[PDB]
Length: 183
Ligand SMILES: [Ca+2]
Image (cartoon, rainbow, N blue to C red):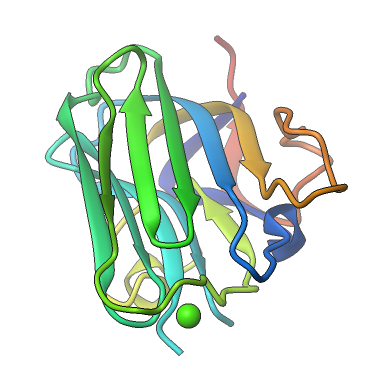
């Protein structure tokens, strides 16, 4: 697992999320541990307004993304801010998205309007970011403090490639204020 602090992060290549057209089922899965009430868990924006992000808001997990005609917001029922490990599964196909925490009833919804694709080829940020306020366009002012493990970034296009937890140490790209995290 990977530990983060003071906006620490780990960056991965935007091809982990190899998107298509028609839109194809998108899977994000991870295990988090943190005492953070507000902060950035994941962000991929275009490097143009399209993005995808997972964050902490009032302890609550939030799934947000923009496809061109308005954001989707999906917030978990309770905070997962308790420093105990929590499984978060965020899924999206086109504008339809959902989140599930552990075994809690899944929250579902969509983005409004006709846009249906995330045109974002930027790096995928986890944990934090070099400068969060700029990257997130004002939506987050910090990363989280804690762990992430069994990160799964899957795009499910007809051939390529099977959905399994990414190796955080060698399968990364950028990185700051981060160290291996035990469990
Ligand atoms: Ca778009």
